[PDB]
Length: 275
Length: 275
Image (cartoon, rainbow over all chains, first blue to last red):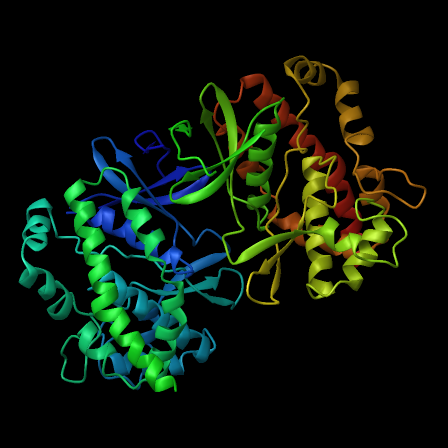
């Protein structure tokens, strides 16, 4: 059941069009960014987290991912960044992803109950760990604001294109499947979070998750773990159109590796500390 | 453009199959019930009411409407009928649609804050009025219940297949368009609501909505009116796949006429009473 968007009505790289009576933003490949966005978002769905709707189809010659606009309501997307740039207390600008600064903003913003926002932030961080997201920057999450009211909600998760090794082509996939050092590098060394420590160093997923004593993070780990269903996750990979076999094999393997080598270790410890 | 479900993996006249990694129930035509369901749910969506996701496509040699399963696991559907049937104070059984008994059940259930359920029910009534639903029976709405918790939510609106004159073949369509009598009959005389007055008679949409002193109904009308966007509604009709021109013309006309002859008339009165 593939969808050709070529003929859809365009709304006055990305193009905005109507499909099934609703607005979708369509994203074109630059390598497997379209696949990453799609597969990652479907995995996030399987985790029971609110996420944008995604479809894999074609536009004229090219595989594309179509992302359903959620701003359609008396709702406007306000990204976290916009909120952050108004925290006068922060010397660094809105785009800067220092974690401590990000957490300060979360506690000091007036859109959402901070507790609620904190749970979401750390839920997403766990999903991003599983998915290997190297670019959850401040423009890649946020809020829905009531168009005709001062009403706020947290926006569904979106922009998961920097997940699942988007740059890994068939050649790279094969190099990793045939070399354990190449594989483990892609577990312990990178991808790393775009969130930063106080030395402006990127937060390493394994190192941070296995050593953190942030209760909010540990709680999230405990919340999300049971919702990880590897059977479903592998089925999603299997059922993804246009994907190469070596790409699927690569994804199946890396998902298993990230789950056992990062998530499981971190979760065991979180268990421990809960006691 | 058009989705074909023919090769979709089946989930071991309706078949349950997997599409875009999610379960859909595919409904087959008996005449225009598939179109009715799809157009009606999309109209409901356009009213800002929560509703099941629908797609129109083909399955083998048949036009089908696919409805996305919202009982994504950890949630079970509990229909109003099942709740109503457990209420011993009610003499009549759960399937009975006497309005006053239904309103009593809404007021005396413990799944949902009664004020919230009541607002939902009347919101749904106003949509069903616009859409001409002759069969909003107690099995056609209800609640979602958490599988591991006592948490209940209201289910998205579903089963809109008895809206929008599903039995109107092309001969009926042309007859109605070329005969004001056949037209007015299908506004003022039928479809009627399946809900019943205390004389055990079906509730007439025009009579009831223009004459009711029920404040909850009138408030619902006031809420939903501003969200009726007829351009959007006609676009939904124009953009429905596979639908014949005569069927489109008929729906365009019937929606305009239900809007002007029932909704607008009732809303003017609601406005006057609110002041």
